[PDB]
Length: 234
Image (cartoon, rainbow, N blue to C red; front, side):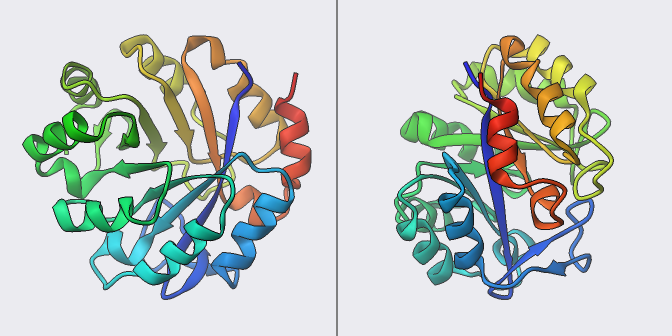
C-alpha cells in the first residue's frame, strides 16, 4: 500500500532529456540513458518509466537503445512513446518490459486500443495527457475513462501537461477527480518538485493512486531517489 515511484528516463536522439509541457524542442540534456537508468536502479528503484520521445514525435526512434536499457534493468520497466500500431506495440513488448503505455497516438485509433487491451491485459496501461480535463491532440477525460473502463483497461497514467517539467508541484485535484471516476489504478505524472509533493501524492494512495512518475526533480537534484523512496516509505 506504499506509493510506487517510477523514476523516468526520456530519450531523444539517443540522450536522456527532460521536456517542459511534453513539447518537442524544450529538451534539456542529461547524458546517457543507460547511465541514468542504472543510477535509478542502484538507488533502489522498483520501476523505470522509459520513454522513446523520437517514436512519440515521429522523428525516427531509439528502438535498440530502449531494448538495451530495458534488458539491463533487473527492475520493472514501463515503456512508452509512439506505441500506436501492431508493429510499434510488438517492438515495445519485445523489449521484455513489464508494461507499455498507449497514449495520444494510440487513442487516435480507439478500436485498436480496445483490441490491444483485450489481447494483452495487464501489460497495457493508457496514458491520458490533459490540459484541464481535455485530452491532448483530443476529447473529454471523463468520457475516455468511462469508455476505457468498459474496454477492460487495467491502469491509467495521468499527466497534467500544464505542470509537466515545470517543478511547480503536482495537480492533486486532478488525481482525486480521476480516482473518483475510475476504480482502476492511477499513476501520477508531471510537476513533482519536492519530497513534500511526493508525501502529498502518497496521501492519495487510498483513493486509487498507485504510483508517481518522477522526472525533472531527480535530474535537477531537488532530492535524491533514496530520499524520495524514504519519504514515501511506511
